[PDB]
Amino acid sequence: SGAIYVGNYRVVNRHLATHNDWANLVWEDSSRDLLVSSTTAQGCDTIARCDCQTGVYYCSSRRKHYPVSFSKPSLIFVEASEYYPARYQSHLMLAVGHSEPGDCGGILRCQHGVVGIVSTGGNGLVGFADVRDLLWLDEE
Ligand SMILES: NC(=O)[C@H]1CCCN(C(=O)C2(n3cccn3)CCCC2)C1
Ligand SMILES: [Zn+2]
Image (tube, rainbow, N blue to C red; front, side, top):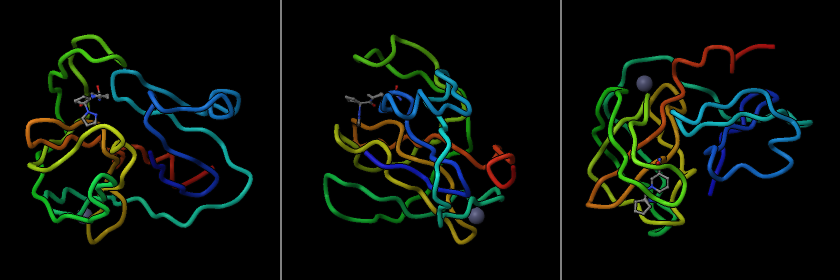
């Protein structure tokens, strides 16, 4: 689990969104595994606006932050699970790292701020849903 809190927005994995998230919905995209809801209190996270390919992510199943090299946001296959059928997930970045159930929502960050959240695992792979192109998170 985990979320990004920027301005009056809460960014979570779409597959982990609560009823309160859906009842206060700003935007959602199943192809990206992302959902944004509105918040009463202002958050402290800042979004990175960059093309970094190195950063650090939080792994809840290890209670550890790991430095990683990650790929550019792309259209990657995610093998069926109980959340989405076989398909292609967009705006996804992969790294070698550990990711196992209980781990989505962990933040990936670079020197500029938050880059995205854990969206995949298995295989000694970590997938992150990028948020750096969502410029509207910084305003209104
Ligand atoms: N983005 C998605 O489509 C993911 C939704 C949750 C399930 N997905 C995964 O990658 C699995 N996972 C690894 C670490 C955490 N979850 C792989 C093994 C079992 C579940 C796919
Ligand atoms: Zn950066």
